[PDB]
Image (spheres, coloured by chain):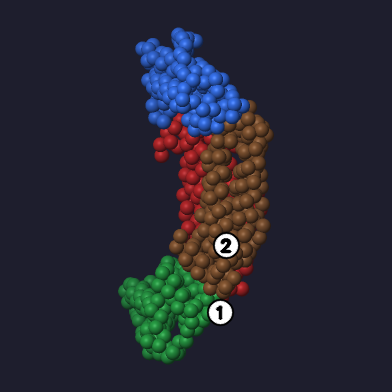
Chain colours: A green, B brown, C red, D blue
Amino acid sequence: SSQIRQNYSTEVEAAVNRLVNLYLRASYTYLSLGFYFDRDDVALEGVCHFFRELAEEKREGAERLLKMQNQRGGRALFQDLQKPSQDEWGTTLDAMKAAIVLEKSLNQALLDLHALGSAQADPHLCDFLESHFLDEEVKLIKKMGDHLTNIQRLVGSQAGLGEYLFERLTLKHD
Amino acid sequence: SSQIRQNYSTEVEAAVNRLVNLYLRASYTYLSLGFYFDRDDVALEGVCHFFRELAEEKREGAERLLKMQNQRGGRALFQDLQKPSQDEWGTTLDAMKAAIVLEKSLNQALLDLHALGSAQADPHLCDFLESHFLDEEVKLIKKMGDHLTNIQRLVGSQAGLGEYLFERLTLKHD
Amino acid sequence: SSQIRQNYSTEVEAAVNRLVNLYLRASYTYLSLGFYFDRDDVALEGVCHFFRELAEEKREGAERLLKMQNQRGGRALFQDLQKPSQDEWGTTLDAMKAAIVLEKSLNQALLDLHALGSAQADPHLCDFLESHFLDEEVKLIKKMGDHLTNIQRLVGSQAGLGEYLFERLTLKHD
Amino acid sequence: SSQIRQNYSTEVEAAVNRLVNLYLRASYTYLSLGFYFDRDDVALEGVCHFFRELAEEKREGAERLLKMQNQRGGRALFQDLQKPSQDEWGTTLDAMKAAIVLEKSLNQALLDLHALGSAQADPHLCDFLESHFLDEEVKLIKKMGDHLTNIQRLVGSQAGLGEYLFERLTLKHD
């Protein structure tokens, strides 16, 4: 193993490596969601921008885990990154419902790793997770929850106008 | 009684103490109205913000009365604060109708205390009330009157879109 | 329930709601303590000040819990707010002793909610509490412990003068 | 009478003239109180400043009334100014006691003039009095009430030390 490793289990090392793949795959998904709203036949700039920023955020989440792996003396392993589940993502409502499901599963994975951390008695991992990932995740899912109920009230009324105005007044103005 | 008290009646002292409870209870109500519009399933940020600022304003109104009580040589008494009448507040229209009724009754209470003040021949109380509470109250109820007729024109048309746009263009932009 | 709620239990939702009531009621207690020391026959401005700033702090502690409730997917419920235990609070010593007892029970409430959070396996709650309430509470109860021993040495020597000097050199100068 | 005079009664005109004398005499009393605390055998600088600033305030109050008399079309009449009731004023406690009694009588005079103003239906006089004198008077009598209970707790412990620390920490530092 390596000279610096201390109270870092193979069970956690392997789970951190699996979580890096999940973050990296969420990133790839948001890259796909963002460039779909840039198509000339979808053309919702604010929505493209929303998903592109989250792509970057998840890539950074994966790098932060990758660096931690190395601080603890673990060794990183990279697996294939499955392409995003869909190639066309629908409307803003369909894309937001897809994104919150995605975030929810990333959050479950953090929660599972944290439970491992405490089972393994690793206070540093538990802290690392609580400090950088657990709250960010709770805030993001609430933002997305908020966006869903606002898209749902607009789109119920007049779907095309609703999508344009949400993108216009919430995503290009908040 | 206390060395500084002069032309301050027990009838007014008791009414000021009752008005502190009313302000404090209005504050608690606006705290409840504001955090309802923050729920992920209501998600109207501007409306949450409107009621949260009024919560603060009413708490300050109660403190201003509390300080006056002490300047006049009266003694403050605090009673229980009843929880807000409702736990879920409806839509922006239902919340604004509830708020203007609330303001109207606070205003009636000021008006009643002012009438006491003049019956008791207390020029300072009458001035204190006219200077800090009576005009603020008249302006606030007119603002709320204005908001009601604007929410009512939007919501008549397309209710969901109407609520989003009011929150968007009047409360996040005025 | 709500689309965003995840790993948030009823035990804890219910417990945050009651802790909101405790904070709000501590807030109301300090309002009373602060305005008591403003009475012309007590006249200790630094003490009035001390307790008024704690009233603001506990009201904000309650709003911070209320905002988290909504981020997690929980639903806020407000109960009546019991009036402060006393109407007249005695001397600075009697007031500090009551205040440290109040903070101690607030702290026990946080400590019990923290224990719930971990029994329920809620890492985010435990983190939120550790980050915003647990340390602030330890530091405040120490500041108050310090203040009691200083008031006790002063007041032991000469009562009136000891209260005046503590208010003058510790509360109007620290 | 004068081309500008309108709804100004001869009763109010005369009462303003008597209030000018009261203010001017209160001013003369504070001039005396202030230079008494400047005597080398009293030597309480903060107490001297306190009463000298009030002397100046009362002379300005008298000038405010005189300018009003002229705006209303009234005619000012000046009577003899009786010398202060005492030539030696005792201790800070005795001097504060005397001063609060002086402000109380000035305040009763304002109140009685206000009552006249309303009996005569003089809205401008009532406003003038409310705006410039009635509140200033309620805050000053509270400050003096605060000062008396602070001097009484000090002086009750060790009279010479109590007077020195009051002058030192409240009047040279508040």
Q: Secondary structure at mark 1?
A: helix
* Residue underneath mark 1: A156
Dot 2: chain letter: B
Q: Position of residue D42 (x, y in %)?
A: 40, 14
Residue type (three-letter) at the residue carrying disc 2? Thr
- Position above or below: A76 against D107: below
Q: Are marks 1 and 2 on the same chain?
A: no
Numbered mark located on residue B149 in the image: 2
Residue type (three-letter) at the residue carrying disc 1? Gly
Numbered mark located on residue D75 in the image: none
Q: Residue furthest front?
A: D3
Identify the residue at image location x=62%, y=38%.
B114
- Which quarter of the rendering shows the C terminus of chain A? bottom left
Is C79 on the left or on the right of B66, as rendered?
right
Q: Position of residue C111 (x, y in %)?
A: 56, 57
Identify the residue at image location x=47%, y=84%.
A91
Would you identify the image quadrant in which residue D59 lies? top left
Q: Position of residue C174 (x, y in %)?
A: 41, 39
How far is mark 1 from mark 2, CA to CA? 23 Å
Identify the residue at image location x=41%, y=85%.
A42
| Residue B150 at least partly seen | yes
Would you identify the image quadrant in which residue A84 lies? bottom left
Is C143 on the left or on the right of A76, as rendered?
right
> How busy is the neighbourhood of tag 1: few (under 14 within 10 Å), some, or many (20 plus)?
some
Q: Secondary structure at mark 2?
A: helix
Dot 1: chain letter: A
**Total numbered labels:** 2
